[PDB]
Structures are given as C-alpha cells and as structure tokens.
Amino acid sequence: HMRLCGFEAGLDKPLFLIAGPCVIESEELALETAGYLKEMCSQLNIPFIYKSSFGPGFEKGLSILEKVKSQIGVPVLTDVHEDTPLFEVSSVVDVLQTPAFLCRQTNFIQKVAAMNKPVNIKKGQFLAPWEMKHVIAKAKAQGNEQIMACERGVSFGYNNLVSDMRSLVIMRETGCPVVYDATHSVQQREFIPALARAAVAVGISGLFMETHPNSWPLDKMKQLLESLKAADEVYKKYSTDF
Amino acid sequence: HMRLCGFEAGLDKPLFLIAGPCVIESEELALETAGYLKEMCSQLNIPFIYKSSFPGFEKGLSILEKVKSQIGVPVLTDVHEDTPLFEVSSVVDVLQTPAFLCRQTNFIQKVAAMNKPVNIKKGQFLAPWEMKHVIAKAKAQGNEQIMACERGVSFGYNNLVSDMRSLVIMRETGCPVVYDATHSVQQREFIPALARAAVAVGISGLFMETHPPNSWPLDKMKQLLESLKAADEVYKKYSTDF
Amino acid sequence: HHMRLCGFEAGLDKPLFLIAGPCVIESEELALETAGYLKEMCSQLNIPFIYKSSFDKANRSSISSYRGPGFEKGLSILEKVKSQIGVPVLTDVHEDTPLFEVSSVVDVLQTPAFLCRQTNFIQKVAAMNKPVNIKKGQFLAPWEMKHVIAKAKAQGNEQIMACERGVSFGYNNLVSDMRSLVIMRETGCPVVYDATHSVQQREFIPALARAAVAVGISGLFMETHPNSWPLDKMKQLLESLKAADEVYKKYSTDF
Amino acid sequence: HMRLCGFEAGLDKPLFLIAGPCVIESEELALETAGYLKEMCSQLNIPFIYKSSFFEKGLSILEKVKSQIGVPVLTDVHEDTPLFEVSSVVDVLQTPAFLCRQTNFIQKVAAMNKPVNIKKGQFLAPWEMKHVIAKAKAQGNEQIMACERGVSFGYNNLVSDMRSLVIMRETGCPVVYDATHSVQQREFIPALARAAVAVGISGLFMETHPNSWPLDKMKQLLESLKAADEVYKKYSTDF
C-alpha cells in the first residue's frame, strides 16, 4: 500500500476523494468550497484532498492554495505544465498532477517525479491502458514510490469520451493506486453519478471530481458520496483482487 | 414495470438472470446445466430464464422443450430472418433477436407479432439513442413485452467497449435494460468487473453465457452472482432513478 | 489472378468498373430511364457498367411503412431493365430471399454488410455460381474480411468481390480507412469501393472516391438518383476519377 | 494565396514537402540528409523545407544546415522552448500534436511572426481546428498551416479520415498531410499519401530514415505524388 497526505491509498484501503472547482475563483469562494468539502468527507470518513488550478494570476493563485492549506487545514493538489516552476509550486502544494495531454512526455514526467512529492499521473485519452505501466515505470525509475494512475476516459470517435471500465482493472498492474476522474471522462452531467458508481463497483483507490457551488453540484456531493461509499464497501467484501 | 415469465422485470425490481451455454451440446448437458442454474438462482432469490441456441433443428427444439418441462424453467433462444417463428414460438418462452439484425425492422416486427417477450439485442454499430427507434417500432403493434439488451459497441478494430451510459440512456425506451456480460468483452477476467459495473449503474437483468471462450465457468457462477446481488442492493438503496 | 464478370474483366490492373443505380426501385419507367442514362454515360467513358437496384432498402423496412413494389414486381422490373436497356443488373439477397428466383433474373448477387458474418448464408449465396459483391460490415476489421471472402471462395466460385463501405467510428459516424483497400487485395479478389455509404456529408463523396481510386481499386459502387450522388453530376465525377485512375496505374507497384 | 519560405502554399499551388529525420543525430548526418533531400526535390521541382527536432548544440547544427545546404529549416517547439532563440535560427515553427489545445501557447508561438505548422491532435475533430487556427491568427500571423496526422481509432491505432483534409480548408490555411505518422504498417505510407494528394492538400510532411520512409525510396514516391497532385489540380472545383 501507498502512503499519501497522512493516509493510505489502495484497492484494499478506504476510498479517497480529490475534489474542488476547476479554476480558483476568489479566495473567499475557494475557502468556502474547501471547508464544505472537508466537513462532508469528515462526516463520511473519506480521506480528502482539495484541488484547483489557475482567472487569477499564477502567483496569486498559489497564495490562495497556501491560505486554503493553512486556514482550512486540508492537503492541496494542482496541475503542472512543462513550463511550470516546480520548486515554487512544490513549496505550496502537497500533490502534483500531470495532465492527460502530457502523459507521453517522459522527461517532463521524470522532472515532476523528481520533486519527491506524490504525483497523480492522468492517462491520456489517446492511451491504451497497458501503456500506462511504462509511463508509471519511468516515473518511479529514480525512487519516487508515491505515483498514482488516473483514468479520465478514452477517445471514441469525434467529440466523445468513453469510460472503458477494463482500464481500471488493467492499470492495477502498474503497482499503483488507480484514481477515477468522474467529471472528465464525461466531457452529459447526468452520467457522472452513474459512471462513478460503476468505477467504484469495479474497484478503485480514489475518486477525482470537479464541483460547482461538466461539474457536479456541491449540494449534491454528499448524497453521491454516500452512495459511492456503500458501493465501495460491497466491492471490498467480495473482492478476489486482493 | 413489465411482466415476464411469471415475475416482474424493472430497474426497481429484483435483478433477474438469463443464462445458459452458447449452443446446445447434448440433451444430458442441457438438463444438467439448466437444473444447476435453477438451484443456484432459487437459493439466491434471482428470477431465472434458461437460454441456448442452435444437434439438428428438430432435435434442438425438443431438448429445449424437455428442459422447460423437466427442469421447469422459462427458456429463451434467438431467431433469424429464416427461422420458422410459429414452430419456435410454440416451444420457447422468450424470443431474442441477434445484434446484427437490430436494424431489420420488418423482421423485428414479425418477431414481436408472436406476442411473446422479446429480448432485442443492440447492435455493436448502434448508438444508444437509436434503440428508442428500434424498440418503438417493435412495440407499435401492441407487444408490451420488449426488452433492450446491451452487448457492447465497436471500439476501433477487433474490440468492444462497454459504454455504461447506454444503460442509462436506454431506460428512455420504457423497457427493462438487460446487460450481456459475456459478449461486451468478446478477456474473461473482466466479465465479473464489467458485470459489477453494470449492476451498480442500475439494470433490470443480466445476460450471461456459462459453461462447466468468453464464457463464465459454472462452478464460479454462484460466487459471482453473490457479489452482483450485493451491488444490486446498493444501487436500489440510493437510486434516484425511481 | 484474373476475374471475368458480366462480359468484362475486373481487377486492380484492369479498367475501372461502376456499379450504380437508385437505392430502391420506384417505377418501371424510372428504372429504365435511369439505367439507360447511366449505360450511355458509362459507354461514352469506356467504363464497364452494372446497374443496381433493390426492392427495399439495405435495412428492410416494416411492411406498415414500406414504399415500393413487391419483391415479385421489383424482380420483373429488373428483368425488363436487363432486357430492354441491355445492361447487367445487381441486387441484394437476404437470409429469406429465394436465391434461385433472383439468380435466374439478375447478373450479380450482393450480400448486405450486416450479413457478412453469416458464413452459412454467405456459402449458400456463393453456391449459386454467380458473381457476388460481398459488402464488408462496418464492424469488421479488414483482416476478418479475408476469412469471410475465403470461405465464400473455398469451393471454386471465381467471381467473388470484396466491397468496402466504411467502419464504425464512435457513434453515428463511418470512417473510410484507406488501408483496407490495400489489405483486402490479399483475398485475391477485386476490391470495390462504396463511395456513397462510406460517409453515411455529400460534399465528401467525390473526395473519398478520388482517394480510393488513387489508392488503387477495381471498381466503384455508387447510389445515384435524379447519401446518393445526383445523376447529372456523375459524368464530371467519373471523368476526374478516370484521370486519377490512370495516374495510379502508371506508377503502381502493386501489380 | 500564402507565402512561405519564398514559395506559395495553397490548394491551388504546387505541392510542397516538409521532410527530414526525426531528431538531429550527427552534424554530419544532418548535412548529408538535408543535402540529399535538397538535391532530390530540385530534380523534381518540388518546394522543400528541411525538418528535424532537438538544445544549444542541436540549434547550432540546424543553422549550419540552413547555411551550408541552403534550405529552409523547420523544428518543433514546446511550452518551455525559448521561442526567440529558435525563431532567430529556423524558418518555420511547428507545434506538436499534443499541444494543439493549449490555446495560449499557440498564440505565444504565432507571436514570433514566423510561419507555423500546427499539428492537429489525434484527439481533435477537424472542425475544432477552425477555433485553434482562429486563435493562432488573432494577432495577424497570416502564415499558419494545419497539419493532419491521424485520429485515434480504438487502442493503438490511428486512422486517416480524409474528410478532415476537406473540412480544414474552412480554416483558410494550407492543409499539410503527415504521411509518415498517420499510421503510428510501413507499406501503407505511399497508399495513404496518394489518397491525401488526390483529395487535395497543400503540402506533404514526411519522416525519413537513411514508421518512416527510406530516403532511397523518396524520389519514386514523390514522382507518383506529383502526378496525382497535377490530376487533382486539373479537375479541382474546390478553388
């Protein structure tokens, strides 16, 4: 099993949630959302990681994540690009994430992993699941043992992503927790709860979700997570995968 | 809410199972298989329909007739454009149209005109919203016992993907949605995973090929059905779809 | 490998031929007029021609909403086209079609794309010892078409053709993978390109036909009516295809 | 029409060629390959742009290529590439397919006021290039081109939807066809290149090796492509 932000991530461990809005709106709104999500997960005993990307400038957005981390007292995650200053971001956030469109940029992935922080590596929509083993293997090649593989859908014809549930099983061969992006593999909102239930019933380590105060409304998050936690318990009771 | 073979089928009703071997091998094997599935399904409170396809055509019909009478179960089979419907319809309880015929409206209506329940399989070349048109014309003449069966959609060459959104969309037909768990991969390791996913999304019935290639072994059926029944209880508990 | 068909030769190295016509037979008058028009146009371009028409669409419709003549009346109209206009005629056959009746009238049988995996039925069609245009299902990979074609040819029918019509690309979309035109040459049969169904959006019909002809094919299949191509634009299109076909044959390394 | 490295690019203009090795291997090898490709294109009267990708040492070889061989040079740029340094050396910038949806990066590249070959991602629908190109031209760069490289088709397969070559004419830009990556299987490169040329394109993009086409088979292939291009231009009603 893998350690991450003070809790354990794994197929046999309790499901965790990466959630937050897409982009940082206001310090006031970001702190309200982060606190609301923290309490909801606390009332459901779900380990929680806050996420939001940069609207406000890069430096100002970094401060809002600094204030969320310190005032709300939650771990924070954000994306990085090939031109992101890794040391400045790493001195603020707890989890780095590589976007799907960079998943084949091996050396950028290696630069990200070299920061010695947990990395959520998003599978590209142009990738077959078995190809993730090599992407993940290159990320771990210098000792970073905190890599995760994030499923976000695969291209299906034009302007359509399909969630191939086999990918959740195949990517267990990476030796990493598999995270399911429930709000991006739709990119049409009424399918988000259905697909999240499917992924959790198949068996995953964590959920990734965008929330709205292709997003799931904040006032509907607790009911959905309540149904997902019950589905997760059923998977673990009958699991023959561990 | 639809009635079928002495039980009711629906998203809010207990999950039912259509299962059996691909083709009828021997009368001895058919009675053993049908009897085995009957005892297992009865002990798990799962309404059960035995299925098998075409052993000469005349000989196969009596074997299904002997299964129906000796084992005491409803029986299902497919028919083609050249199947003598009255002869087949006078033996079996449920007709099924193969996926490659789903666009042959003239043939679908002839099948539905037998006034038996019909399991209409969606073609791998069909979008889910197209089943509304297939089912509507199938029901146009009063047959209120039509079901929609998902079996996967083409994904590039030599690959089927199970788009779980189809299970939600086809609810708009007003018919039970059946999930073919053994053809959506046609690769055996994913059968339980994909069955768990579909049941968690919410379906009316399961369709499974079982033998003691893309078949599930008979001696592993009960453990699998146990996990699917638990996932089905979780779906109905939190469902907002009924 | 050389193949004869309706009095002419079909092949990657042979002149391009055309299967064309309306989807369904409307009237005897309309079928004879259309067939006669295409016959003169193809003769004046030196393009071997086969007229095609069915009594119902490829996906047969409910009788409660069916527009057209009977199976029997449609068969008679094709006989008069063959006889009055003097052209070879092609039509579809389904699993419930009387093959001997259709075979005694038409020159070329055609199996629809949705039946390509029905080996039993394909073998019965090939047993008629007539030319067969076997359409590739949108759910088939090109290498699977070799097995479909091979089983049809396994007992000596030397007039089998492979017809490409596009493959499923996500929902409600067909893509024309030009690689299949190359792969299916390995069946040892003429490859025919369905230019009006590979889109099933009309703007692309001439473009996709040019592409297929430049890749190298044996024949063209086209739906034309006055995703059908209009009858009064067929000649300009065919003229540009012949120029692209000559260029393909001049530099070809495939034969 | 559009000007590019001293020649005109367009559906109605003669076909041009971007060609070269994937990455700079040797200074010696780059000069030989660029010289070989330059000679071949002259014997066929085909406008030619040399391409290879990389940082300081690789950038230096491409200038010696530009100066010794006397050909225009093209190279890729990434989000962290210093654009001004590369732009002061090469003649044409190229954005890789995986960056096409990074709108702000596309504009930073186009702001160099050099011609730019924007590769369509394998995950993009053709009609989406209209939006990508519009943002690229938004600050006046009238030297943008759209490069087709295939679209994802299931797992581990790229298919060339020839319709995209027609659709992308609506961007108002020359459409370039990548004949050596739309496969990513080597026997199909000439077949697919012929098809794209018969559909009608502005230029060819090709990876060469002394999923690449051998350098000693380039001339026979290009000879057949120029003939197909002439036939397309003779009957074209698209311009």
Image: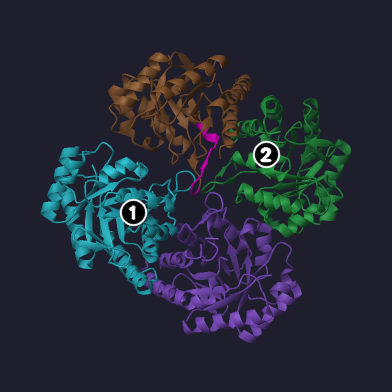
Chain colours: A cyan, B purple, C green, D brown
Q: Is residue D114 visible?
A: no
Residue extent of the magenta highlight = D154-167
Residue D185 quadrant: top right
Chain letter, disc 1 residue = A
Q: Residue C109, image x and y in percent?
A: 78, 48
In this rendered view, identify the residue nearer to me: C98 or D206: D206
Is residue A121 one of those drawn in magenta? Answer: no
Element under disc 1: strand
Farthest left residue in view = A71
The subunit letter for the residue under badge 2 reads C
Which residue is at a point 39% across and 57% down the rendered structure image? A171
Q: Is residue C250 left or right of residue C104?
A: left
Q: Are marks 2 and 1 on the same chain?
A: no
Residue plotted at (36% across, 42% down) = A101
User: Residue drawn 51% across and 48% down?
Assistant: C170
Determine the image quadrant of residue B65: bottom right
Determine which residue is flagged by label 1: A149
Q: Is residue B97 visible?
A: yes
Are dots 2 and 1 in contact, CB under 8 Å?
no
User: Dot 2: what SS?
Assistant: strand
Amino acid carrying label 1: it is Ala
Question: In front here: C221 or D179?
Answer: D179
Amino acid carrying label 2: it is Tyr
Q: How many C-alpha atoms fall within 10 Å of the one at disc 2: few (<14), some, or many (≥20)? A: many
Question: Any magenta on residue D160?
Answer: yes
**Label 2 sits on residue:** C193
- A93 shown above or below B71: above
